[PDB]
Image 1 (cartoon, one colour):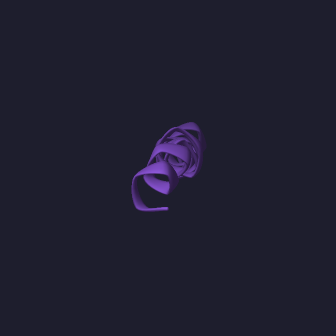
Image 2: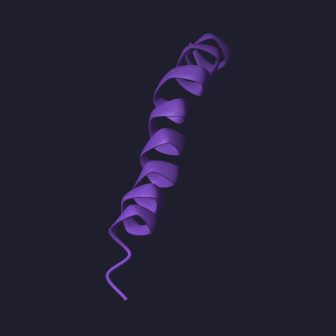
Length: 34
């Protein structure tokens, strides 16, 4: 079942999360710790 778009979109779900951590968490994390 080579449903490309779903595997691609699973990788989107992963990458979007990961970079959202690299951007919407990094600065306030940095401010909190130093």
